[PDB]
Image 1 (tube, rainbow, N blue to C red):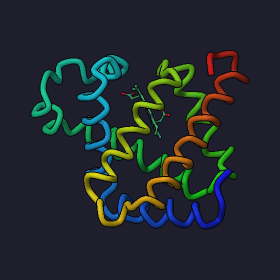
Image 2: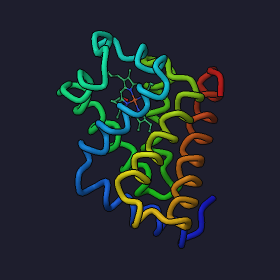
Image 3: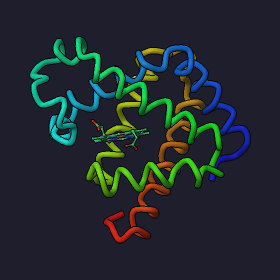
Length: 153
Ligand code: HEM
């Protein structure tokens, strides 16, 4: 449910992410992990990362953050008619990776925090509100696909 206006504010601020996808991605995962330490346990390759410093040095963490936001940008660019891009992600996240809807909320918070921290001037009240609705739409559609597949939404 976003207006055309809100989608344009989302994709305008996503333009900033697109100019450095891996750096934003690495910051999002570090914020996720440092705010909610338990999420780190879903990534078997990152169990030895015992500090923010180790996290910043990890080339695999930065690659995973890049892969994550490149996929999320693909979903945002479809503005809601994103069923095709969303399904495989809910499939893998519900079945292979075992990621609960709650962690999708934590990572939504980390994305907003990263955007606010890196682009304070470009991420004013209207852009923030629209990005919150866009990520809420992503979470709600992920939740609904989880239900369809027989999992908890
Ligand atoms: C904005 C939300 C997210 C996006 C767009 C996203 C995207 C992706 C993509 C594109 C992949 C690789 C392809 C695939 O397996 O589907 C992936 C893998 C993975 N994701 Fe996510 N993800 C998100 C949130 C999460 C969260 C919150 C967690 C757990 C805290 C998580 C855990 C994982 C794991 C464990 C893998 C496999 C990595 C490996 O094999 O080492 N994801 N994710």
